[PDB]
Amino acid sequence: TRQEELAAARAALHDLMTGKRVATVQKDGRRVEFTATSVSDLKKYIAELEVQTGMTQRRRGPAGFYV
Amino acid sequence: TRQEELAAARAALHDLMTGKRVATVQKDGRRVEFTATSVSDLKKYIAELEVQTGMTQRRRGPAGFYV
Amino acid sequence: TRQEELAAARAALHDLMTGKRVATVQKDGRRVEFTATSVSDLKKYIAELEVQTGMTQRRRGPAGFYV
Amino acid sequence: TRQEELAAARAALHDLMTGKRVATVQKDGRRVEFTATSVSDLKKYIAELEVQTGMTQRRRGPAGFYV
Amino acid sequence: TRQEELAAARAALHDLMTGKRVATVQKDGRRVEFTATSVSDLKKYIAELEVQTGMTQRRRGPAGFYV
Amino acid sequence: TRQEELAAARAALHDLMTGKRVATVQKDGRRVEFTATSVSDLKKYIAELEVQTGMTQRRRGPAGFYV
Amino acid sequence: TRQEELAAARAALHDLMTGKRVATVQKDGRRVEFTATSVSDLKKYIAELEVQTGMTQRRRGPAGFYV
Amino acid sequence: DFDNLFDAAIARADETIRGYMGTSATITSGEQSGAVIRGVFDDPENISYAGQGVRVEGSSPSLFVRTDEVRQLRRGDTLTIGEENFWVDRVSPDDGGSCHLWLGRGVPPAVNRR
Amino acid sequence: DFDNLFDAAIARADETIRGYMGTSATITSGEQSGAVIRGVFDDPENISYAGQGVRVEGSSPSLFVRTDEVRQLRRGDTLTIGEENFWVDRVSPDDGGSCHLWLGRGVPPAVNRR
Amino acid sequence: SKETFTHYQPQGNSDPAHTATAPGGLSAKAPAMTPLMLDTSSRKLVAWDGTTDGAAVGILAVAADQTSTTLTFYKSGTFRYEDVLWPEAASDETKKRTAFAGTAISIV
């Protein structure tokens, strides 16, 4: 249950980036709203979940040097 | 009784992160707000809950060096 | 009379962390609200109330060194 | 009239800490609220009165060293 | 599906920069609002998604010197 | 399809500078609020778009020194 | 359109300085508002558009010294 | 359970308000017979003059309990709130997670079913 | 799509509030026959007294559905709210992105037109 | 209280044992050093049933399961018959011995 979690979180990230993270909804007496996260913490959450799950490698180890 | 609360906190983290951490709910004449927190505190709480629970290893004792 | 105190403090910590510390409740003509407490201070209170009780240790003294 | 002061202060501290310190109450034409006090200074005050009254020993006189 | 949301995000950025990112819309008790972002994060998101997708080169690797 | 974007952005900057970047619109029940941008990021967008598009020579590099 | 653009911008700047940078216009049922801009940014925008325009001398090249 | 993502929130809201406000009363008679249910009892005023002066000043008790246990409540059955005694005379339709209960005093007047 | 700059935002808001608020109602009979729509259902309580005491306390169901999915809905056909079934008594004109479907209970009473 | 420190000699020849990686579709926990064949329908990697003849493609190098999107397996070399996790379907030894014929994998 990590792949669909990744998909949902990434879709939420993309829509928040573009236009589609709705915060409040109102129905003239039936209204609610949700708290909002931050772009940076959402991105690092995405990175953490993808690295912990079984998808492909995304980051290598340091960097070699030679003359 | 650590597993159920660990799972609940993880699901709440995901739900808050994506779009659905509802803060106030209002039906006609009936408002109620649940206080909200940051995300770093939630992450450190879920990490400490997992580590105190008899879960798998997540930490390594420093790191030795060899030539 | 401290075991239930610890239980209440832990439950409050858990619900506040996930979703369930209501800060205001409004009924038509009947609304009340409670002051909110920071998570760090609640953790301080949890730790001190737990250690002052006769329950088992969660803490040990400083560690020495040897070659 | 000191021990009951101590008990009331501790009870109020616990109530504030968990969820219970009611800030405001609204009835039909009854808006009554009380200013909140920070947990840090509340703890300082309760500790001060506890050590002022005839309570048992909590503080100790520094700490000597010996080889 | 990369270029589609690339173009969507670019268009959203152009809109926000110009004039008409809808912060909130209401009509007779039907009120909704969308969370806002920052131009910096939107531009860096555009850049990173462009790098992830198969767009042509935009940045290069340092620059050597020679007399 | 970048020159018309440049023209639109320049016109938007001009009207925003003078008097004519509308924030809110209200018609007795229908209201629309648009996100507020700044001037620095707007002119940064203007500069980046004009340099990337087929706009003519406007920028030159370093400087020479001689006696 | 540089000349009339400059004239309109300068007149708007003068009006903003004096008394008539209208922030919002409200008639019963219809309320709108325009975004508010700073003054220094407007002044520097005026200066740069002027120097871009083929108007008269406005700047000079550093300064000369002689005993 | 709730196919809205919002009815769960409204149910949490209603249980929270019923827990932090109101009282618990024991249903009397009816198909529920002996049972205890917690609601939020309020009671405004109502005045009627009838003739010139025949003022019959009374009260309009309401309970507003959740919909789950209010089912198969019917009308003729009674209800005791704390120490006082009442009886249901009207039930509002569900607003999503609850409904208002209107309470008369004393014994319900007859049945007059047929 | 439409020369509004505002109705597009209205439609997006309507879709969002349909998604986050309301339930899925399926229609039966009529030219739509069987179809599934998302709409926010409400049921305010209304009472009439008529003569001496004729309390006929009832409900006024409304659904607030988008006109696009309910084009040529007519009036005679029925509707089902999940397990419950209704019948459209009237349809409001669209306000720009949707309208309100006002419903009655049971079966529509005859036709009575010719 | 008789601990036997048996030496581990998985391979049985001097030929090199190269590895390769490919996405896998194991439906059960697959221990290392296990024969596996390419799926007929999905063309994915699954443990060899022991009944299909010649369909086996290699020997699993490292342990994996359903969660493992891809996996590494031996593609060249020669191993011993004893330390191969044969499926229980494989009854007679001779077909197991000849199972990897025609590939870079051999058994002894």
Image (tube, coloured by chain):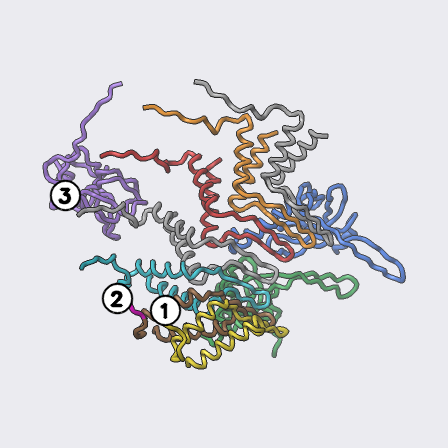
Chain colours: B red, C orange, E cyan, F brown, G yellow, H blue, I green, J purple
Please give the residue where the numbered disc 1 appears in the rendered image.
Answer: G63
From the viewer's side, name the closer residue of H49 and I84. H49
User: As shown in the figure, which amino acid type bears the numbered disc 2?
Assistant: Gly
Q: Chain of mark 1?
A: G
Residue at position x 83%, y 54% from top?
H57
Label 1 – label 3 distance at C-alpha:
80 Å
Q: Is residue J56 visible?
A: no
**Label 2 near label 3: C-beta < 8 Å?**
no
Q: In the drawing, what numbered circle is on residue H104?
A: none
Give the residues in magenta: F59-64
From the viewer's side, name the closer residue of J106 and G44. G44
The x and y percentages for residue G17 are 54, 72
Residue farthest to the front?
Answer: G67
Label 2 – label 1 distance at C-alpha:
19 Å
Q: Chain of mark 2?
A: F
Q: Is residue H8 magenta?
A: no
- Please tell me whether residue C47 is drawn above or below residue J49 in the rendered image: above
Please give the residue where the numbered disc 3 appears in the rendered image.
Answer: J76
Q: Is residue E43 visible?
A: yes
- Please tell me whether residue C11 is drawn above or below residue J7 in the rendered image: below
SS under mark 1: loop
From the viewer's side, name the closer residue of I29 and C40. C40
Please give the residue where the numbered disc 2 appears in the rendered image.
Answer: F64
Quarter of image, res F27: bottom right
The C terminus of chain F - image quarter: bottom left
Quarter of image, res F29: bottom right
The x and y percentages for residue F15 are 47, 74
User: As shown in the figure, which amino acid type bears the numbered disc 1?
Assistant: Ala
Density class for disc 3 (Cα within 10 Å; few <14, some 14-19, many ≥20) is some
User: As shown in the figure, which amino acid type bears the numbered disc 3?
Assistant: Ser
SS under mark 3: loop
**Is G17 on the left-hand or right-hand side of G2?**
right
